[PDB]
Amino acid sequence: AGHILLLEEEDEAATVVCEMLTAAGFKVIWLVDGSTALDQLDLLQPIVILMAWPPPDQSCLLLLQHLREHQADPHPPLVLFLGEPPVDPLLTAQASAILSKPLDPQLLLTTLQGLCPPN
């Protein structure tokens, strides 16, 4: 099991992404605002967080601020950028994996499994 957080705008675009992950058996939440994610993120506390980087994006910036405030914390999540890669090196450094044209959604699953959580 594992909760995945996704920030994106446009029901059509979000539906596509959700369809791929949903098919993978993973649950993804579609949020149109970073503040909304913080409200739930704290409650669900996901191990992976994906955020759109395209121009129509901007709410993801608020989420990044949160990470900066509590960047240091056991069980370090995972940040993935959808679309094109960030120009600033600060986001790239904090980026867990850049997505764009990955072979099958299986690569994404590999990143999630790469956590190896023992319980």
Image (spheres, rainbow, N blue to C red):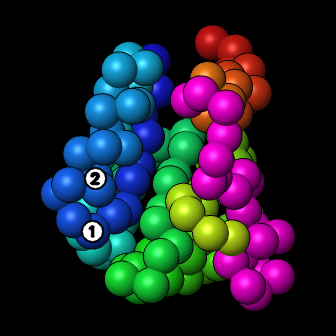
Q: Is residue 118 left or right of residue 54?
A: right
Q: Position of residue 37 (x, y in %)?
A: 33, 62
Task: Specify start and end residues of the magenta stretch as a single range.
Answer: 86-105
Residue 24 picture quarter: top left
Q: CA distance from mark 1 to mark 2?
A: 7 Å
- Write the residue at 26% across / 61% down: 31
Residue type at mark 2?
Ala
Image coordinates of residue 75 in percent, x first then y, are 68, 42
Q: Residue at x 72, y 52 (%)?
A: 97
Q: The disc labelled 1 sits on which kind of residue?
A: Glu
Relative to 116, is 40 above or below?
below
In the displayed structure image, the side of residue 45 where residue 37 appears, left or right: left
Rendered location of residue 71, percent (x, y)? 68, 68
Residue at 50% across, 54% down? 50
Judge whether residue 40 is colored magenta: no
Q: Earlier in the sequence, mark 1 or mark 2?
A: 1
Judging by the rendered image, the residue that carries numbered circle 2 is: 14
